[PDB]
Image (cartoon, rainbow, N blue to C red; front, side):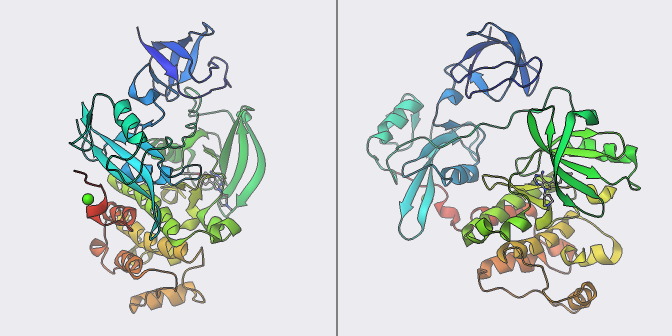
Length: 430
Ligand SMILES: CN1CCC(n2cc(-c3ccc(Oc4ccccc4)cc3)c3c(N)ncnc32)CC1
Ligand SMILES: [Ca+2]
């Protein structure tokens, strides 16, 4: 007998799922992934619920200040998001000491501006050995009144949002009829991209492929692999229409591409540490792809999507294997040798695209002119706004020998703490 509680409001939009409000208790009848079968204690209706909108009663995730599954860097980003203030805090899982918790608090010093500082909580719980607490609420309730040591006293828990609703149960392959493609977003040499609607009540984005040599069969073989590359900085692949012409249904990304975003009004008021934060997100996306032994092939700003809350996501991973040299590494251009290391090269140019607010690479140069410029060891110069240490990453990304190029793991780690010294990652307190 298991009892869960609703963390958010949810409105039913399918045949057999349930409507519930925040605070609603319900009984778990069945566990099966993103959708669970429950029994509402307020309506007594048996039906389906999203398994990420609930958690066990009295458990840790029921608390407003607790954030499950957040890395130190995610906590920093969520707490620097609009709607938070001094003392905005969260207790979360430790990313380094597995099974322990960490406190992240929004601070301000006039020399850097707003920051997020992190504290390790030790197993009973304590941050300062001087002061121990029985529960995590006792901890919180203490530092909430004055800061017995902290950079700031605790004010209000961090701003959260609804997680995205999980795609319908067993619906990887859908009939084309479910779609209303409402507006063309883009059109290229291989197909179109549309804002659409799935079964009247779910906004999505649809990539329609122009029926080329891309074998029906051979595509699904690769699409079923893209379905398994689920990361927060990879775009979410929802479904697929299996009959030629092929449709690719993904999550709708409000702000379009990174390229069109950097070139826009709102994109031009992004300070440099945000541009780097963007890069960090992408390097996290690639580190995952790298971890998973996989290849992007077409890494550039036009294939990176931006969401309404400015989270960066990677699109068309792999597509180039199934289906523009200024982004392409020499070995890839010369002998068709695409590796994760040729992506690192592509990541260097994207880095520059970011730092130049989307400006075309090698300005004034032709594709042939670029190729001969490379073979003589020419590289792009550092622009006015680029810090010197960020140029090194680009220059390291652009080494003649693939093996000499850094990993996305190391790149992510450098970009993540770009403004922080290793020693300042966690504040130590006596
Ligand atoms: C002008 N322009 C075309 C439309 C625009 N775009 C593309 C996409 C897009 C790109 C690829 C895509 O399909 C795949 C994603 C990952 C792997 C394979 C295919 C789905 C949507 C998109 C989106 N989801 N939401 C909002 N805007 C989007 C990007 C810039
Ligand atoms: Ca320290």
